[PDB]
Image (cartoon, rainbow, N blue to C red; front, side, top):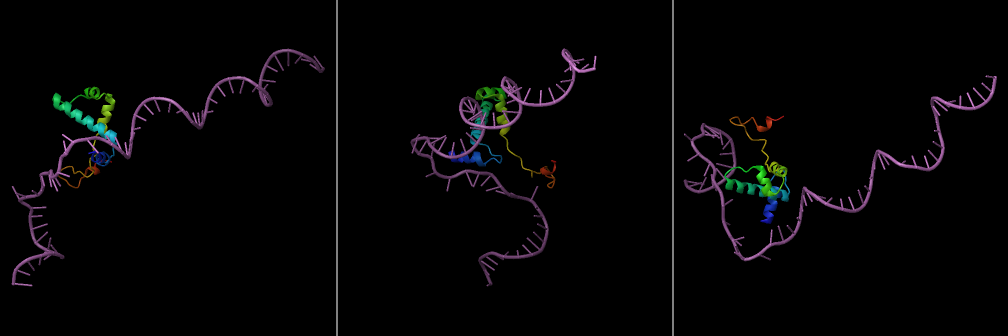
Length: 89
DNA sequence: CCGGAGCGTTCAGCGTTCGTTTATCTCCCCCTGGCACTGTCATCTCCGTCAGACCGTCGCA
């Protein structure tokens, strides 16, 4: 489990994230999911900040860092030739 | 009728203040290493192209 999650931290994401930041973001994700299934609603970032004992600015920074890139080759729709990479200057 | 005083400008003694560095002390980031009841084979793909060719492949003759 240790080696698999270490390689998941160091290799799964294209923009590499250090292992401590990976465990921080997935702990935040799992406690957010727990609060969502308990309260039945999306938890406010302030309550997440108090329950994680971190500052709200740290919480929103963590949510910002927890993203996934989108490929430049995703088609828009019916047309195959018009790409997502040709709409950005 | 030069002489002195006051005034303008310009420099040599030491006296303080800056401009730019240096090693030490907190706070944080980041990577490698530990966990000891057992727990020893996933995963859904893919169908109502399509049109015929080009080609190698392959078992029957």
